[PDB]
Length: 127
RNA sequence: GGAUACUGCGGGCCUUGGGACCGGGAGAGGCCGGGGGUACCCCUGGGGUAGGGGUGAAAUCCUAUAAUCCCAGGGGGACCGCC
Image (cartoon, rainbow, N blue to C red):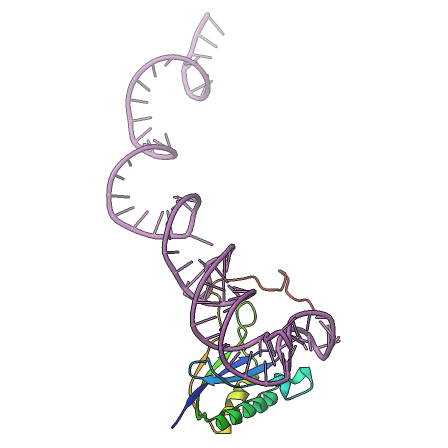
């Protein structure tokens, strides 16, 4: 029989997390970060690191018996940035190549109807 | 002593300036009461294993008394995105 899961991707300017669950999101299957596959902190969001972690997670999922997968991609959002990083697309293509079938794709970046104050300081960062 | 255009004083008239009223509409004008929208933070439960965050690069910091991440619930305070 064909079973479907869900891949949550959390992408940032500093790391990428790929997490595969069942359709309910209450049972976890695999979880891999860009910091498990490199040793430089400045490479955690490299799309190659993302590809590698995606491959590991996909192979573990297949071993567990997962065939299809829906996708929810996310940036931190809220008061932080609303734009994903560059590892998300890499991870998606890597999941496709690993051998899983892909279903729906959606963005779930949480966005403020009007909310809290960000960290700048009325003048932002000045480096 | 004389004159009466202008100004002042006294008395009548006018509607052009201003004010009052009727009508159908506009608008984030103000105050009061009620109902909501996402997001964020804390707590409690379930899943899961080793890093998460952060930078020009890093480290102080959180983490094995189980973090980041995913799910189900409870509470609280500010704000009202796109249009």
